[PDB]
Image (cartoon, rainbow, N blue to C red):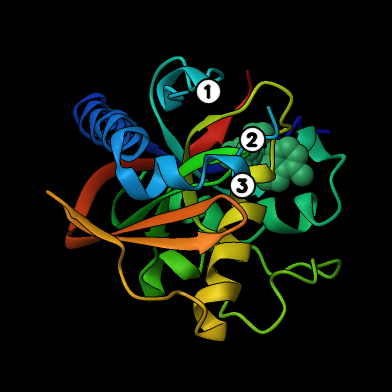
Amino acid sequence: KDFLPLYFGWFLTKKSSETLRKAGQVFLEELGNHKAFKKELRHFISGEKLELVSYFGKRPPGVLHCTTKFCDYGKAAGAEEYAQQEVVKRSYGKAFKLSISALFVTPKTAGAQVVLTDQELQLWPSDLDKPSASEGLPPGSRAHVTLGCAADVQPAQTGLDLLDILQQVKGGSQGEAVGELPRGKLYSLGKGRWMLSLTKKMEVKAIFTGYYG
Ligand SMILES: Nc1ncnc2c1ncn2[C@@H]1O[C@H](CO)[C@@H](O)[C@H]1OP(=O)(O)O
């Protein structure tokens, strides 16, 4: 039988990767410097000034991606079923534009929120065993690009952290913006969670394909 990928997803172009990576780093430098962030450090780490670029020391080495289905070479529940879909096979190798609406930070991860189109949502997995954090929220809400994570954090965390942030915004606990950065308004959501809502959404170009590793 055929070996499936470790995961499927949208792999950003060199140029788009660079643009997003740089905006992520700017965001981390700006946030760590902001009075509102500094004031809440006791809620971010249990340990002065914290350099977030250093804090999120495990970062993608190269091109960035937005994962659809983690398959673990076929071992993950739902993987075979996902891989066999016509839309996945038809879409393999095709170019898409992804809309980034926000950047976020938590004690565990730094990421960018992706808002998928209906066409793109046909490639979002619809599995049997789903998480309770996805509960209530529209499919594809988890979609994101991971920009870094803290030293002992495992893969899958950024998505979890996004859903949590969205479950909060859904609750109306977003609060008034506590500052304005060049790219948009900054929100403090508590328990070390921060979100920049970009005034102007970023568009990144990407290719849908499978990563083996
Ligand atoms: N259960 C899982 N185990 C490992 N990675 C997973 C995963 N579910 C989703 N992923 C995603 O698959 C990619 C490779 O691990 C990562 O983008 C990761 O999401 P993450 O960005 O939130 O870490």
Q: Quadrant of residue 114?
A: bottom left
Question: Is 187 placed above or below 66 here?
Answer: below
**Circle 3 sits on which residue?**
43
What kind of residue is marked 2?
Ile
Specify whether 74 is left or right of 28. Answer: right
Give neighbour class at mark 3: few <14, some 14-19, many 20+ (Cα, 10 Å). Answer: some
Say few, some or many: other residues with alpha carbon within 10 Å of mark 1 (under 14 / 14 to 19 / 20 or more): some
| Rendered-image quarter of ligand 1 | top right
| Residue 14 position in % (x across, y down) | 25, 24
- Tag count in the figure? 3
Q: Which residue is mark 1?
A: 55
Q: Quadrant of the C terminus?
A: top right
Tags 1 and 2 in contact by the CB under 8 Å rule?
yes
Sequence-first disc among 3 and 1: 3
Alpha-carbon neighbours of circle 2 within 10 Å: few (<14), some, or many (≥20)?
Answer: few
Examine the rendered structure and indicate whether residue 101 appears above or below residue 182: below
Mark 3: amino acid:
His
- Disc 3 + disc 1, Cβ < 8 Å: no
Residue 24 is situated, as x and y percent measured from the top left of the image, at: 32, 35
Seen in the image, is 64 located left or right of residue 3? left
- State the residue in front, 139 or 118: 139
Q: Is mark 2 within 8 Å of ligand 1?
A: no
Nearer mark to the viewer, of 1 and 2: 2
Q: Which mark is residue 45?
A: 2
Kindly state the secondary structure of the residue where label 3 is placed.
helix
